Image (cartoon, rainbow, N blue to C red):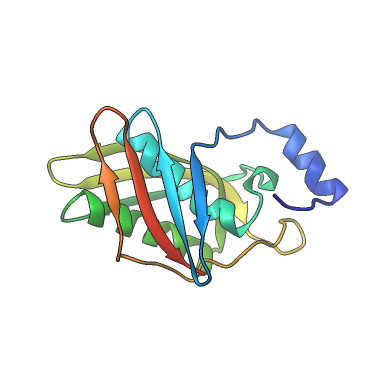
Length: 158
């Protein structure tokens, strides 16, 4: 939860809220993200939105521009890692993109390939509430469950 300007509240009211299927467990130097959904694809996209949700109130981001992230791994855990790593790099460099919403179109469970898409705009300290900088994705405790109730767990450094 953040404190919003009047302008930020107005943008949040103009766009549909994103359903939140994630939660945080805070520690001194890192945070565990837990995300879930009806599909593994939904658990992945919720994990990405949980990550960006730690940096700002993504409800205040306008869905002006579209950005695609495609990636591969050697298993589902490393696929998740590189998926989050690539989205974090879209934010931290180049176009400094912050997604309001992320969608995972497909995960190839055989080859560990993924296609995803996000809608958003350039991050800006004046338009977007300041949250906490995500310094890195860590790989020490990736967890992926891909049975009846898909869910993922990841630790990010702050």
